[PDB]
Image (tube, rainbow, N blue to C red; front, side, top):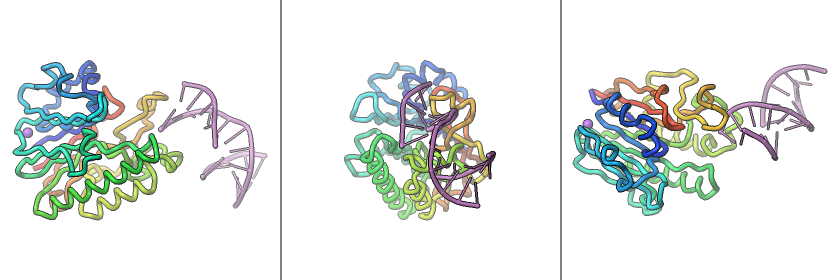
Length: 254
DNA sequence: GCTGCGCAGGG
DNA sequence: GCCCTGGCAGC
Ligand code: NA
């Protein structure tokens, strides 16, 4: 069995101060995917950049302290692809696509759309490019695993306050519609393969002590193509892990 | 973003 | 009446 963990750290240096490595060796993921590291590798202390036992790959945004994704993996991929072939998406440090023989692993930090009409438009177009990219790789005979911060809660059950948020990027019908669309192309929300209950969240606002009162959303997901779901054994939320406004999620396969 | 609040329809 | 849906300063 291969354990993969995904975590929108919201600043890899910041989380390093708040027990990152201690936990890292504590959870022992086969693969560790990180989103929103807000760093370039040149900014990271040796023992944070290079964790013993793992190969590490970093893809920072062009812009400083912004976005960025990272992957640590005991067994290296035979290729890491850091983009979809669309410059405006490929320069924000949002994409890592690792080829691990059995599957392709997409580590994606999808755009947040709250800031502006442009940032939602960017978000929705990024969603479109990903779907095409993953569909092309899946239509060609590959199994795919997609993890990361989609920045959208799919259904009213996937957030504490569904009604007040229907007008705000993150729960817009256009955004929820796209997740339906994703699933109808033959992709499975692995968490809801085993768990249909409320109160399962993955992010909470820092403002209003939102986390201790479990007022949050499930914005982080593990998707696999429908041909691959029979290889998934568990999908769970690591709710007790602190450090970010997000908590880790996990997957184990075969 | 969450939590209040005033306000306005229903019902 | 009351409830319980549906712009905003305060954080
Ligand atoms: Na590995």
